[PDB]
Image (cartoon, coloured by chain):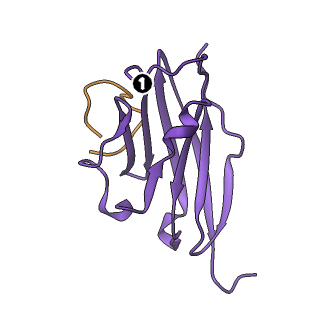
Chain colours: A orange, B purple
Amino acid sequence: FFXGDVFYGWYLCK
Amino acid sequence: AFTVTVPKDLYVVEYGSNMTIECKFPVEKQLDLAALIVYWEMEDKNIIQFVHGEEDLKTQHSSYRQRARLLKDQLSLGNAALQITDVKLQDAGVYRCMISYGGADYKRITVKVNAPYAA
């Protein structure tokens, strides 16, 4: 998941 | 405050069936598609990425191609509903729904998959 800081730290996709 | 709710936090689904897991978020009379961001993930797999009123399929994990979708018509009702067809055993686990709509929140949902001969 990329998109800047949208849900920063809530996800694991890299 | 902006809060995302789950009607059910544990889904027990049968192998090979269809699953629809739902997250609820507040929506006014009309839906601002530019403001809505929805992201469904499990483990580290990009399930559904929804931006500007459309799903982004370029980042979707191969495990879910034509297997999962966000039901856009339910968003009108304040419902981010993930539908996955032909559930496999590898679909069991913890799913996260992240929703930004002015405010932002997210919730966890656990899915157990029942084996074909378990009932």
As rendered, which of B54 and B2 lies closer to the eye? B54
Crowd around label 1: few <14 · some 14–19 · many ≥20 (10 Å): some
Q: Look at 35% across and 32% down and name the residue there.
A: B51
Image quadrant occupied by the N terminus of chain B: top right
| Residue B29, placed above or below residue B4 | above
Task: Inspect the image, locate mark 1, and give the three-letter code of the amino acid beneath it.
Answer: Leu
Q: What is the x, y in percent for residue B3? A: 61, 23
Q: Look at 36% across and 44% down and name the residue there.
A: A12
As rendered, which of A9 and B65 lies closer to the eye? B65
As rendered, which of B2 and A10 lies closer to the eye? B2
Q: What is the x, y in percent for residue B54? A: 35, 38
Left or right side of B66 for B105: right
Q: What is the x, y in percent for residue B95? A: 52, 49
Q: What is the x, y in percent for residue B19? A: 59, 60
Left or right side of B60 for B71: right
Disc 1: host chain: B
